[PDB]
Structure formats: structure tokens, C-alpha cells
Image (spheres, helix red, strand yellow):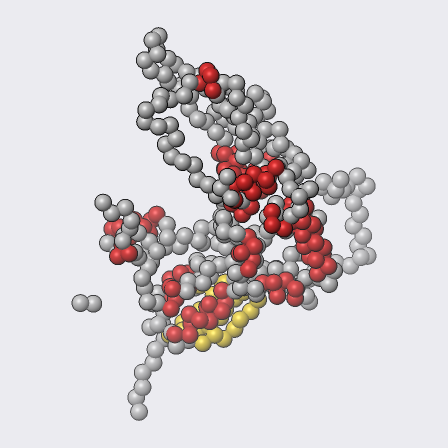
Length: 75
Length: 50
Length: 109
Length: 164
């Protein structure tokens, strides 16, 4: 019963306190799931740690930096 | 990089203040013993204490 | 993969049928930044009203009284400022010369 | 009122002005922001537009020596300028060329270089808050700046919200 396998990327998103819901909205369509949402101690920013398919990760950074007014940044 | 400058709305607050938009820091080293007494000279002060 | 002094509606851009780009989700900037020129009270009305909850959750128990006292001082300044009403709700002994000139302007005399 | 120099011919053939309108930039922006605030105040409080060209086609233009010369003009547009907060800017905010005869702030009579103190700059930044945006960094203007506009020019495409 042979099957195929695809690569999954790990994504960390640095975003302000309201753009996090916009990040959850954007990741909803690229077959992804958010694993961790953690507040940064000593800073008003949050961190979003998630997985994404690498075939869906074309234009992902531009989608975040356009939908969140350039505030959220992702690697 | 994200400029994290936070504006001040109240002039009666001190200029350096923990504005609670900043998230709270969660709380919890080779420290020598007090017996080996190091002593500074009396004219030693921290800088700009006045 | 395969003369007209107005501007026409066919010259328009951003006619894009994307759920991400029609609702572009503009920033409010920590509930502190303001868009210039558009009225500040109207901007405080059209906000997301989310960071106010973060304030009243994370301010100190004395800082709610500090915020209320600062708003009372601001309302005192607003009441000192307004003491510029319309002539339909003012009296005769308090009606200044600017108000009489606006009253003359209202009836086109 | 404004008093300017004039170059003129011996018979009155032509009359020149011979002055460049030099201003200090943050003072100028603060003054126009005060104008913006006062005119918003005036439309929320009070309109009759003036009737255009007033002087008819058969009458000559008015003589200055008999009609405008001894008539005192009306009240101009000035903000209240509260003396507690606006104290460093109160004595010079509505002058013709502000701080011109002061050796502390302006280099001289040609009115070319300026340097200010920091509470004065705080006051001029506070009064000009209506004309200035709340931006703090260049994480704004992403794909909406001059290099992306030149790229869209060279590739013959249209940015959403950008030009064609």
C-alpha cells in the first residue's frame, strides 16, 4: 500500500495583540494548525508557533505582511 | 524591527513606568560568601546619585 | 496562465475579489495611535473596543480610579471649553456678539 | 497685514516684490495645524460663501490711499494658546517671521538657519498633532513604497490601491 509524503514547515509569527486573530484567519486556508500561542514576557508582542505544508507556503509571508498592515512578521 | 515605543497619556505618572500593555515577567549563580569581606573606600559612590 | 473634468470609474484599481484584501484589517496601534484629521471622538467610537478590556484587566486597582479622575479632569476641560453652544439653547444675557453675528448669518440678513 | 519691499520703475511701469517666503518648517506645520483646528471649530459652531468677482467689469480697481489706508482690519484667525502649556511659544507664535531678531534661535536677518530648544519642540509637536500620522516605523508602506511602485511600473501591473 504505497503512499506519498510532503514536507512540513515550522512557522513562528511575531505579531501585536490584535493581529493574532488575523493570523488564525490566514492560516485557516493553507491546511495548517496552530500549536502554541505564547505571550512574550517583558514585551507587548505574542509568538505563534505552528506547522504548515511547504507546498502551501508560497506567498505566505506576503499574505501576513499585507493582511496585518506589515506589523506581523514570520519566518 | 518592530518599534515598541508606547505613548504616555498621563503627565502625572513617572517617565519610567511599567505600563501594563507590557506583559508581566514570570518570576523564579556563583554568589560568594559574606565572610570574605570586601570593603570599598569611603569616597566610592555610584555615578550621578545626586 | 494563458472636456471630462471627472475621473471615470473604469480607471479605478483595488477591484479585487479577495477576502483578505477587501477587509484589509487596519491597525489601531495599542489603542493609543490615531489616524490624523479624522475626528478623535469618532475614532474612539469606531475602535474594536478590545484593548480597553486589556487595560481594565491589567491596570492596578488604584489605576481605575486614576483613569476615572483623568477622564473627569478631561471632562472638566471640555466643560470649560464649551462654556460655543447653539443659540436655540442659550439665553439672552449670555449671548455674545459672535453668537449674534452667527444668528444674523442664519437668517441671511 | 504684511509689509514687503518693492522694486519699481521710475514711471510706474512695473512693480516687483523681491522677497522669498522663508519659514521654519515645524513652526509652519504647527501654524497650519492650528488653522485646521480653528476651522473645524468654526464649521461645527456656525455658511455663506463670498460672491465672486466682486468688482464689476466697468469700475476701476479701488484706490488704496482713500479706502484701505486708514481702515483698521478685522480680527484674524488665532488660537487661544493657553498660557500654562504654551508658555515657550506664546510670545512668537503668530508673528510675520517668528524669532527673527533673537540671536539665540535664528542666525540673523536673512533668516536661513534655525535651532530650537526641546520643550519648544515638544510644544510644536503637540500643537501639530492633527496634521501628523501616528506612524513609528517603516513596517508600514510594505509593498506600497517607491521601489515597489517602480517595480510595478517596470512589470506593467497594478498594486491593489496603487496607481496604474
